[PDB]
Amino acid sequence: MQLSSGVSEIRHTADRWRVSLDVNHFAPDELTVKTKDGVVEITGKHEERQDEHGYISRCFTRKYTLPPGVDPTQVSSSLSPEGTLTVEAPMPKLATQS
Amino acid sequence: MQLSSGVSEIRHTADRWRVSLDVNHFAPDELTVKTKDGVVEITGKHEERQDEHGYISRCFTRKYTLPPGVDPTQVSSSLSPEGTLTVEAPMPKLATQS
Image 1 (cartoon, chains in turn green, brown):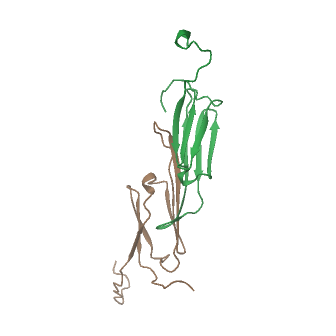
Image 2 (cartoon, chains in turn orange, cyan):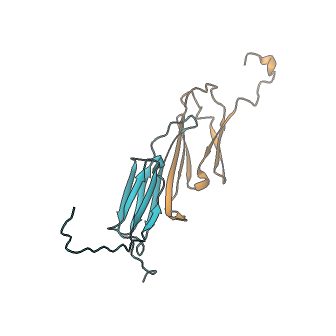
């Protein structure tokens, strides 16, 4: 920015943030990622699961409402069987509240 | 009170069973205990959390279908703010089903 001399190149690969969500370990396939105009939510729920002390199923919801401008067009998400949901992308370095 | 205690049916045959459904820690009031003919279910869902790492919420569901091991009339439940749900009571000592 401005200091073109600090980049020289017209195109560069920087300005990237990496936030992570952890839950799909309970559901790798029964997980749903939906980007809602800046609202980042991960849907994860399972049906009647067996357990040591009974039958237990739960639904998990984590909602990230980032108004500062977590760009919806440029925010993608990686998910590994570990239930590691990485949301990596370029975004407004506002880092305000939650 | 004394009641029509015509006889002293004092039978302390109360070994008593004791199982716990600890989860309401995430829900003291948002918890609903339901005993349905041997079916013990604990209804509990959290409320949109507000944390710097995300606004999260979940729902817990445990279904203990114990026909020949849990009585519907004499089963009570203890709950403490700590979200500890003890189900204590005298139960029909049955042997398998059929």
